[PDB]
Image (cartoon, rainbow, N blue to C red; front, side, top):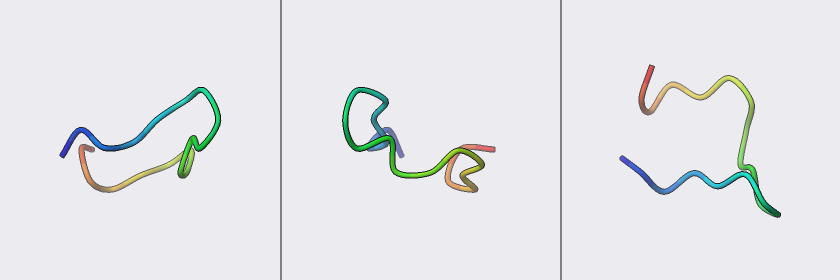
Length: 19
C-alpha cells in the first residue's frame, strides 16, 4: 500500500509493504 511517507514520518527505511 502507498501509506509510507518521507517528509516527517518516513515510517521505516527497509519496508516490506511494497518490496
